[PDB]
Length: 257
DNA sequence: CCTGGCG
DNA sequence: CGCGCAGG
Image (cartoon, rainbow, N blue to C red; front, side):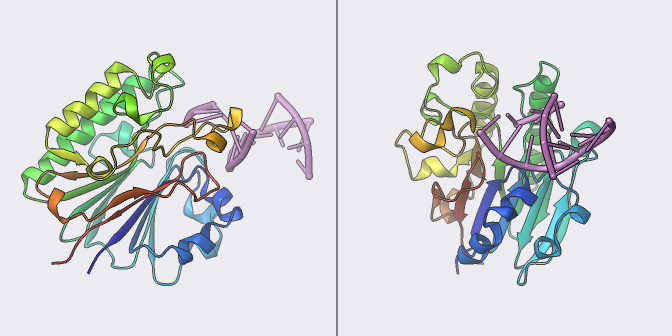
């Protein structure tokens, strides 16, 4: 009895719907699908997206018209669904879906991009900070956590095609690479690295300069568990072939109880 | 129906 | 490049 979970930074759900989304969503059959950067409120989506037979859908849209936003489809509904950490700034941008699956917490997080500004960065890290204290509190409470989404940060050099030219860009800043160390040091396993240790494995590629076409990308989308849960995940992979976004989907699968 | 934020 | 958004 294995639970397949998919994360995807979708970059416009209305757009991905126009590029075969649902077709894939039913071909690939995941018990939980977490989507990030949805760029929509639910009343903007076609009913075909709001209502997917088999799945209860949940949407956390920002209070900024078609910006950010996370979503989730799921066969077995969560016992409850939290949408923020407890700080307005982070809570109001459709970035947080913590969904209690009475077995584990599934954290669907779209972490802030810090490319575009120093004050939008910073926000990214303070967001990171707010997330950690939170996940800590939950797994200290003995709750097992699965965290997926768009971290917007390559952890180590191996997590992007061109680390060296990228030292100064947000996404591979030593400041942000630091936090993931902290994050892991706090007892979280980068589930993908539990299986693959090869380079050139990515989940993001710049649209401009047609980067995807030749694998010149980054690994920004992650599946994480707590050390204590490491045992019960039996594959974290990357759906490198799924199209219609500058990111791509990443898969996990876990176990019964 | 084009065209000119964030990522 | 791509998404969406607003507003001529």
